[PDB]
Image (cartoon, rainbow, N blue to C red):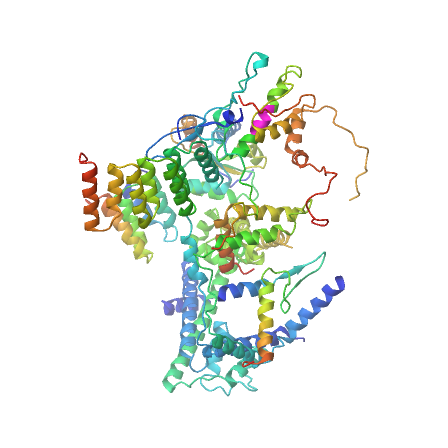
Amino acid sequence: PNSGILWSEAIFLEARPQRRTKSVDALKKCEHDPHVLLAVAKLFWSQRKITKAREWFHRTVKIDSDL
Amino acid sequence: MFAEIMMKIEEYISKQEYRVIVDANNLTVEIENELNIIHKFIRDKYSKRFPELESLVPNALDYIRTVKELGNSLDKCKNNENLQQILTNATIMVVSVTASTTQGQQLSEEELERLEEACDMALELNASKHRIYEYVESRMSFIAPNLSIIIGASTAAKIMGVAGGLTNLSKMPACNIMLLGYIYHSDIVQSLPPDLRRKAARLVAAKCTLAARVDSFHESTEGKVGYELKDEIERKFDKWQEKPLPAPLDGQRKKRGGRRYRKMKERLGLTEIRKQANRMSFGEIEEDAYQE
Amino acid sequence: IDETYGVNVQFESDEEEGDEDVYGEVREE
Amino acid sequence: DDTNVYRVTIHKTFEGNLTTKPINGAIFIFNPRTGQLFLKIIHTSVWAGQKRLGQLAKWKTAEEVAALIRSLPVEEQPKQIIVTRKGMLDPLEVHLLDFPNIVIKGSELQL
Amino acid sequence: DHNIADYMTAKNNVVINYKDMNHTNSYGIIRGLQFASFIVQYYGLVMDLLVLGLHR
Amino acid sequence: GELDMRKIGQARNTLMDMRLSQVSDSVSGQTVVDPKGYLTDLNSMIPINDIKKARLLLKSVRETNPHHPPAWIASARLEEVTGKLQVARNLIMKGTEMCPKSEDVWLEAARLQPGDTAKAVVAQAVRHLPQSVRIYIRAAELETDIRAKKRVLRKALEHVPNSV
Amino acid sequence: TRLYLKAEQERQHNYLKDGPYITAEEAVAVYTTTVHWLESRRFSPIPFPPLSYKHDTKLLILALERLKEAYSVKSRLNQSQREELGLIEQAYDNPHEALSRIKRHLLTQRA
Amino acid sequence: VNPKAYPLADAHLTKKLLDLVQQSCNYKQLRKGANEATKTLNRGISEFIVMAADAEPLEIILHLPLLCEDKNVPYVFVRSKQALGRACGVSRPVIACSVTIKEGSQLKQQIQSIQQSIERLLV
């Protein structure tokens, strides 16, 4: 459960109305992860919300800029 | 996106998996907002020809019918048989009284043609949304009739589609509740008083879940369990909505004054009243006779 | 506010309130 | 002494607010005729609660004052409660109503 | 202000209860309203201005 | 059958409202209200017995010790922290006359009074307790001029030349 | 009381069915006369309750006194009267909270 | 019982599951009800999920094995819902429940033993 890439794959393979709980579960299980933050940014950009996706991308760049 | 969904709905209705009903429901939910925006644009465009048409007709379809039947010519409001099929008699009298004193300039030919084309497009979008809702109700009655009869056909269809499948809908704890949410959007919930409708939404889960669970197998194809759950939810919503004097026996004092009894005496009693002395001096007071 | 417990005098209810001008001057603000 | 029970030690600070925290619940009671003194020691927090006015402390002190007389025998209880605090004498006199045999007299002399 | 006026008029249009009877007041005005005095005085001013005449 | 008789009333009310709205155009001084706009001011307006007990204790300490400039400073701080500043200015003016030759009480009286009164308060504090560096610094700080501050600094150097 | 309540019921129903009795353009004419008179007076209309007022708390104190005067002198008060007295005391204790609640009710509450 | 409820535990296995559910609910680590059990299974914090075969309808508990196919958790069905309700301490019968993992609980070894013993019944 403590894997960022597996949490990102589980958030990307899930349904689009079911990803809002999967992203919260990935943030609660594996917090401060760059892959989970990138998956949350991609889910926010796919939901036509650029104002949250830009903040999620900024938090992903500030948590780990080496990704 | 609307043409392919309409062709899929026509191909499904001409032959008589589950993603087509969800696509038709999403297309209807988008076409409702598109028709509302088209009615708002028609009210903003035809405000110069009839500024009182929006206040007399608050509905979108009634205002669209009044703008498509009359248009720039306001002479179609006296003894007209076509205007009586959209609005009532008092609404027709109010529209005639508003068009008798309008104080508005007439539009051009191109603006009236664009308004008529927008009204025809809104009517075609409403007809396509009604046909998609009928096809989704038929697919919900064919797939899961218990959830379609308990909370609503569209609700059931939306629930399954949102769940991504009847097998996921039953799996969902809030089965048949798809935030469409569907628990609140539930007709049985809608039947409950607006405030109780929310409570009915929570209570809808049990019935909706049961309906989905039953619909999971090949049992209850007629919808008897869903009708029983809807009747139970309606009974719960109806229940949620809408002495001889004692014998004056002679007073018996406390057998033994206890600390708990003293605590009650400390809590309740005449301690504050005793502080205020009711004694009155024999001599006259400084106040007047009837100071009160 | 000295460290004496009695440094702060006890505040007994007084200055009786009342539409009566104790100072005896007609206020004009 | 009514003020002793309500006495609150106050801190001193150039910038910080003075901490007028209560000291203790003892009223510094004395009885030269009895050859002893009474120390009704109570907790400082119990003596003065948070946002407790002086009248509230006096009302609570009256209950404790009557409690001391209640614990003591009627003969041993002071026949005359000479307290110079005339303002606090009336609640004490009201408290003294619980003991009709005992009497309360004003104390012109202040200990 | 329009909001205060709307609130006052809405308060003037409320449900009236009794021992066993309840109805809705729409034309009448609750004399028990704390602000009813102001509205009655103002409307009486309206009739005064109407009857007396602008110049008068 | 019997139609909705309320329809006629609704139509009449709508006609009356429309006529009134049309007549509102001639109202040059017509004004509106902003409850929704006020909603932001009501949400931004978001920030008793203990403060009253502390004020009563400060008043009892000032009555039990009139010559205590810590008690006068605490009473001035309690009166200026809540309520109005006029009671704090009156308490500072009472403490300056009741407890003379105090630097902290004079500093609190200069900080609580306006500058036209603070100049006279600093002059009275220099007449009552001269050679004070804090009172001279408060007088030079409440001058708002170059020549007045230079004269105050020259007077402080003539009074107490051993002040750094 | 019962008869008058009934009569007012069918009176309100008749007003609803028959509509307002203010004749068309007659209430409009009355309003025009009123606004012309006001313009001749040329006074600033009263605005919404401002955040800052000269004696805002004084008005709350006067209102609290007026409501208290209904049953302050009474020996006892009913349960509804007791609740009203408690509400008045709470409003007096916290004038700012009561004022904020009153303004919110004014600008939001309509039922 | 219902044939759709699978797997079914024995008498001593149901007694051990009821004792583990009572130890989890007494230590504030158990969730009663089928909705809370399925929410804890979907959230990824439920260590084990127990069901009951005496449920009307039995398909409403059918989400409890299916969530076991969605989170890889051992599932088991009790014989009666009234014993699981009393085991949960609730007077009302419980047809479903969930023993969740805690931050270093003392009953982690018993929960692991119950998960190892409940995974062999589904064969």
Q: Quadrant of the C terminus of chain F?
A: top left
Front residue of F111/E45: it is: F111
Could you tell me which residue is drawn at 40 percent across and 58 percent down? B19
Front residue of G15/E40: it is: E40
Front residue of H4/D25: it is: D25
Q: Which SS does the magenta portion mostly show?
A: helix
Instruction: Check residue F64 for magenta coloring.
Output: no
**Highlighted magenta segment, given as a residue range:** D60-65
Instruction: Check residue D61 for magenta coloring.
Output: yes
Q: Is residue G4 left or right of residue B275?
A: right
Within the image, what quadrant is residue B272 found in? Answer: top right
Name the outermost residue toward the top.
Answer: D35
Name the outermost residue toward the front.
Answer: F127
Q: Is residue D101 left or right of residue H74?
A: right
Q: Position of residue B28 (x, y in %)?
A: 43, 65
Q: Position of residue E26 (x, y in %)?
A: 62, 67
Residue B86 appears in view: no
How many dots with numbers? 0
Residue G75 appears in view: yes
Front residue of F28/D23: it is: D23
Q: Quadrant of the N terminus of chain F?
A: bottom right
In the picture shown, does residue B74 fall above or below A21?
A: below
Q: Position of residue F21 (x, y in %)?
A: 49, 76
Q: Position of residue F83 (x, y in %)?
A: 43, 46
In the picture shown, does residue G15 fall above or below D102?
A: below
Could you tell me which residue is drawn at 49 percent across and 86 percent down? B74
Could you tell me which residue is drawn at 49 percent across and 64 percent down? E3
Could you tell me which residue is drawn at 48 percent across and 24 percent down? D24
